[PDB]
Length: 119
Ligand SMILES: O=C(NCC(F)(F)F)N1CCN(C(=O)c2ccco2)CC1
Picture 1 (cartoon, rainbow, N blue to C red):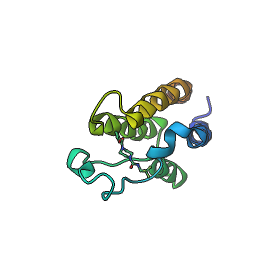
Picture 2: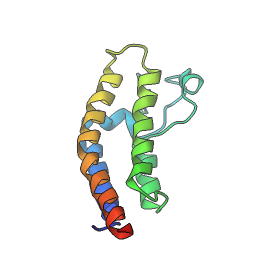
Picture 3: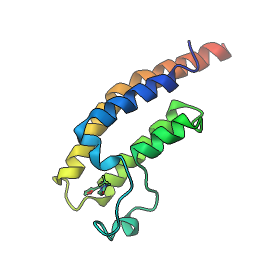
Picture 4: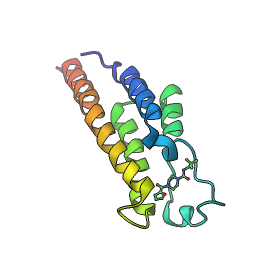
């Protein structure tokens, strides 16, 4: 019932994601010389460095907000991909499965902690 425990859990999950080769493309902004149409397709860029930064600045109030930004990384990849079989999109889908598998307990424990607080 630790209301604050999600933050370190999310830091540790981000560490795992940064160790994962699949996160490579999703660590930093898109170079518009390499992908000139990116910001035509993608209004709201997100990468894992921005997520980690936001977390470490104390600018997430809950793991749900972090989860919204991470999911934006994945939905941006799905919007930008020219094919459902592209290399980078395929990396996004594996990483998304990994993230969802690991974040599920973090969200459950946080929401449990908030309900116990309100009890
Ligand atoms: O250039 C980058 N990342 C920055 C870098 F290279 F420094 F890591 N990206 C990731 C986001 N994109 C995609 O989701 C995508 C789907 C299909 C093809 O690309 C575009 C390419």
